[PDB]
Amino acid sequence: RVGFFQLFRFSSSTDIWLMFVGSLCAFLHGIAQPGVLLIFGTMTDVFIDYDVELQELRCGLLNIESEMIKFASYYAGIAVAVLITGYIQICFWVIAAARQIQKMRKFYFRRIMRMEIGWFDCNSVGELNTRFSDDINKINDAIADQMALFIQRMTSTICGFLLGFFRGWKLTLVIISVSPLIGIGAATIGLSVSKFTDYELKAYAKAGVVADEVISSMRTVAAFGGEKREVERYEKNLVFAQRWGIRKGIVMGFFTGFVWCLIFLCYALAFWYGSTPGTLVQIFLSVIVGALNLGNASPCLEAFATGRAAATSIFETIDRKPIIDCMSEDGYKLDRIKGEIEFHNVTFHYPSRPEVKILNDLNMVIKPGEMTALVGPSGAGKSTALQLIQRFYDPCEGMVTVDGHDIRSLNIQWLRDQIGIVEQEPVLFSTTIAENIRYGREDATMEDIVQAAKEANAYNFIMDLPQQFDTLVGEGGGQMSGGQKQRVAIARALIRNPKILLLDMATSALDNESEAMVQEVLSKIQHGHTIISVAHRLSTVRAADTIIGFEHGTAVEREPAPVRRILKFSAPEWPYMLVGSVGAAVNGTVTPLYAFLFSQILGTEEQRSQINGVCLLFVAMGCVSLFTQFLQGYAFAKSGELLTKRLRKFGFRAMLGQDIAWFDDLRNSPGALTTRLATDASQVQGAAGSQIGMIVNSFTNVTVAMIIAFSFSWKLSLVILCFFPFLALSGATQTRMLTGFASRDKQALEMVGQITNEALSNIRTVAGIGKERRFIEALETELEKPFKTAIQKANIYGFCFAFAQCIMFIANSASYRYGGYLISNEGLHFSYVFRVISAVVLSATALGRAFSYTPSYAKAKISAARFFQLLDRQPPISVYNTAGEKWDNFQGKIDFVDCKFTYPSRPDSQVLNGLSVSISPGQTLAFVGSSGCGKSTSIQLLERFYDPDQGKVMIDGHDSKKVNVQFLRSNIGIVSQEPVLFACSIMDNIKYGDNTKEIPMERVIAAAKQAQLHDFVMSLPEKYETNVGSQGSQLSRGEKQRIAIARAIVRDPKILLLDEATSALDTESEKTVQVALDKAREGRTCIVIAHRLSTIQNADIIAVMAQGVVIEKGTHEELMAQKGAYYKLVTTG
Ligand SMILES: Nc1ncnc2c1ncn2[C@@H]1O[C@H](COP(=O)(O)OP(=O)(O)OP(=O)(O)O)[C@@H](O)[C@H]1O
Ligand SMILES: CC(C)CCC[C@@H](C)[C@H]1CC[C@H]2[C@@H]3CC=C4C[C@@H](O)CC[C@]4(C)[C@H]3CC[C@]12C
Ligand SMILES: CC(C)CCC[C@@H](C)[C@H]1CC[C@H]2[C@@H]3CC=C4C[C@@H](O)CC[C@]4(C)[C@H]3CC[C@]12C
Ligand SMILES: CC(C)CCC[C@@H](C)[C@H]1CC[C@H]2[C@@H]3CC=C4C[C@@H](O)CC[C@]4(C)[C@H]3CC[C@]12C
Ligand SMILES: CC(C)CCC[C@@H](C)[C@H]1CC[C@H]2[C@@H]3CC=C4C[C@@H](O)CC[C@]4(C)[C@H]3CC[C@]12C
Ligand SMILES: Nc1ncnc2c1ncn2[C@@H]1O[C@H](COP(=O)(O)OP(=O)(O)O)[C@@H](O)[C@H]1O
Ligand code: VO4
Ligand SMILES: [Mg+2]
Ligand SMILES: [Mg+2]
């Protein structure tokens, strides 16, 4: 745990001043209650003197009406002071914490974006997102207003017992004798809670990785039907976190019960050993003041310990010093850079797998102003060489040089500025195309972007879009074709006009014609550029000034009722709310009942009967409180824990059942959904935990107090009851102004999560373009939006909290004035009635602090409304729907009958302008065409990700809209265009091919052998159990593709869909994979999409697609005889 006073590292002078003033006001508000104790003690002696003079009837000197007019004036002054002090106390403390938390978040995100690339290989994005969302929120909970409330309660407790020292002495000695026992207990309990919080936070962080990966790879999850297992993993992570919250609630519910018992038993000990009426009453009331105000301090200690744990978690990251510092200025920068790069005996190991030597004494020379082609098998280390030039890592031994200068002695920012890179399988950011291209150079005008698109061969298809250059590419570029994404990435790298170009397979997803068009300009710009391209095409390899071959590391040349819904939702927790409510009601009854009883025991001496009766009352009120406070604090915490895990599980389950179109909406980005999952459950828990116990306690206390008050004098009680409707008005008015704020803040909070996930998951791309500052500024500019509303919520909360206590004290002032009227004018023996009524009303003053539960009530209502809006949605394509046609014998016959389709996110241009094709069972169809003509769109129709608008897709003579989604998907095996893996072992990534059953390892090994993958996995430490990293990023692209092929093959599907399954492989491995795939596609229907036309000549049918329409259809020989578009496509390549 961190030091508690170390939570204020970010506090400035203004924060210190605010804390000082708020603490002074809290101290005054705390001493306000011993003042009312003194006033109550003074009135009793006056009554005793008046009663004795009446019953003896110094006569006529004292008049009760004037005396209690003075007392009412005292109470009114106390009310005004309490209003002022409470408002300032809450407002200043809430404002001070907000600035510190904002600085903490900005520092956290600014430090995270500075770490070296190797740091992210060991630290998941989901864990960082969960930290940023929830741990800083817990730190805020620790230091916002629980600190002010704890200061006030401690002041009241101290002044309550210190009053018994300065007056009515010889009884506080026993309290001093036991005070270390309270202090020692609260320290050990605080230690226990922090340790529990560490496990809770770790389990919650592990739960956020699963959700993030599933939401990012929903398309893969939906294709293989793994929603059930992903929900199971999420529940497994959540159950561990829920179990520790229960123990935290237990240990914090024992603390509250221990305090009451100890105080009351210690006073019972003090009274029995021992042996004016206005001193006994003060002592009796100080007992309950101390016990009640120590009991209510329990929520603050738990908040402090939770904040300490979250703070050590957050603070470890901020104080870390990165090995490779990009924003630092300790480096040299050259002038007139030639661009020559040289490797000198470079040996490299990856920090995640240090037992494997990726580069072994590698030596190359890359002459400036020439084209160098890196060729080699998958896994030879071609991608690692470029990352070393980028200085993402450093060689274990050896030296990388530019123009003869060591890479380690150069300014990092300048070096990465001089480099433009097209990463293998590029990634774009969620914005318009123009902004994505302008991410390279922010000083680029519109004509610069137009020229960049012209060189990237992107101008034509961009201008053929409904929103030219302003089309939204989507999350990661998902709402684009692979070739379009690649060409936009090429335009991004070319707009910088760099000296060094690193094209890692920059034409992988392009057809022959567009690849030739790109390569023409690439060969044209050679005089002023140093170009290094990883390539597989023979045409790319030729016309290259230098060819360098890689082999194993060596290189050689050549909604409407949120509360009612949650009340119906929390039904299975009735037993725990029943016992908790009983405990809270018993707790609320004793506080005014105690005041009533000690008035009876005092009445108006004896060692035998009076002392014993007082002592037994203390023992009973100690033991019963010990049990019932524990019951309340444990049962309500358990109910909250159960409710929040059910909320989280059901939200995750409901998210997975939505259609793919839902996941494509810009309001449903993966970051936003993860932020929804992480935060909306905690907010409902905050209102749904022990706060219901507090509310029940307060309501029962007030009800019992007024019940006893009405049974003595209904005339006086009506005055006090009349003030209560003011409490309902202010509380309802508080939530009314706060729900409007909570609606506007959640949108900003969700959009902040979008920025964090986008930047942290694409850190390699961000470092490649070198736009860390851009994302920092974007996150900062969106973090300020709730910050302006924070001060207004602080003012509203402070005013309502102060006004509640002000009304409580004004009620007593009015009651005193009315009693002054009543006793003098029309009253006999009424002095005792007013005494007991004032006693019970006085003792029912403090528990009206349930107004501090309210400021989170506005948040919980919005969170519940949003949770129930999603839980009720009915997707057009329901994977959870059990209704649909399911026939026994599946044959894999596919028919397209005049299919017309438009993407919902882009409804101004349809991508399938009538598509008619038929594949007989056992045949193979090869889809060929230009980049972006709709080949992948047709595949998504078969998987039922989308439904055709006009037309139908027929499977075995059945319309696809009437076929069961699960049944249809269980018979299809798909290799996506750029496949994504899960952060697990290789065996688990292969075993995902067939969920709902356990695949034996023999079948996994056979599938891996088929995909030409067994030798690579065998040559690794931890064979078949190596973690592949996030999205399979700790592997080469070819190995990831081969794992995907094995995953598709292992399930043995009736229909096999391959969407460019060799785009990352080299020719030598491609031939072996094709030979193995021929057996895979020998007894089943298959659809093949390929820009490599050497792998489709064996296909039964070759259909050429153009703008969503088939133009030619036939075999290889027939299509070459026609000299059509297929012949041109083959010839140009
Ligand atoms: N971040 C990483 N952590 C650990 N190992 C990695 C990481 N990135 C790559 N590797 C490993 O380094 C080796 C070299 O693969 P590399 O990524 O350099 O591909 P490549 O040889 O250029 O091939 P391809 O054509 O498939 O991209 C592989 O064994 C790969 O698993
Ligand atoms: C009136 C009595 C009873 C209570 C007074 C409490 C006040 C004076 C206390 C409570 C919280 C305290 C602050 C807590 C944190 C900070 C930041 C730290 O880096 C230095 C100390 C400093 C600046 C403290 C100054 C004193 C402080 C403001
Ligand atoms: C404007 C605000 C700050 C005024 C607040 C005044 C209050 C807090 C002060 C001012 C006068 C004070 C009272 C003056 C005299 C008596 C009688 C004495 O035997 C017991 C204390 C008692 C009952 C005092 C209690 C506290 C008191 C009521
Ligand atoms: C609108 C809601 C908040 C009701 C407000 C009632 C307030 C304003 C009223 C109710 C009882 C009133 C008090 C009753 C008796 C006296 C004694 C007199 O010698 C001085 C004024 C003083 C102390 C009054 C001040 C105003 C008072 C406190
Ligand atoms: C079910 C439990 C929790 C209910 C507890 C309510 C208790 C504290 C209340 C409810 C009704 C109350 C009684 C109402 C009327 C009378 C008569 C009066 O001359 C003295 C007080 C006395 C005797 C009250 C004592 C306290 C009392 C019994
Ligand atoms: N989810 C989507 N939302 C909107 N437009 C999309 C989406 N996916 C693809 N597109 C666009 O619609 C067209 C469909 O082409 P696509 O199927 O991606 O091409 P290809 O035939 O190369 O696989 C392209 O213009 C592409 O940019
Ligand atoms: O390279 V494509 O636009 O046919 O996925
Ligand atoms: Mg590579
Ligand atoms: Mg595609």
Image (cartoon, rainbow, N blue to C red):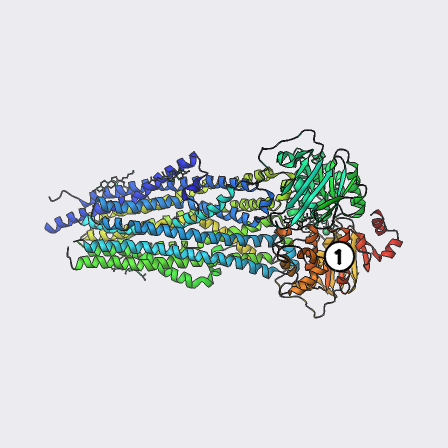
Question: Secondary structure under badge 1?
Answer: helix
Task: Answer few, some or many: residues within 10 Å of disc 1's Cα (few below 14, many 20 plus, some between 14 and 19).
Answer: many
Of 536 and 761, which appears nearest the observer? 536
**Residue 644: horizontal and vertical position, in percent?**
48, 56
Q: On screen, 706 above or below 461? A: below
Q: Residue furthest bottom?
A: 888
Instruction: Identify which residue, 595 or 138, lies in the foreground.
Output: 138
Identify the residue at horizontal 45%, vertical 50% (top origin).
857
Residue 608: give x, y in percent of width and height: 16, 59
Question: In this view, which residue lies farthest toward the right?
Answer: 1121
Residue 276 x/y as whole percent: 17, 48
Residue drawn where x is 62% and y is 34% of the image: 409
Q: Is residue 417 above or below residue 597?
A: above
| Vertical placement of residue 483 versus 567, above or below | above
Asked whether residue 916 is in view, the answer is no
Of the pair 277 and 995, the residue shown nearer to us: 995
How many discs appear? 1
> Mark 1: which amino acid?
Val
In the picture, measured across the screen, residue 302 lies left or right of residue 830, that is right
The residue identified by callout 1 is 1073
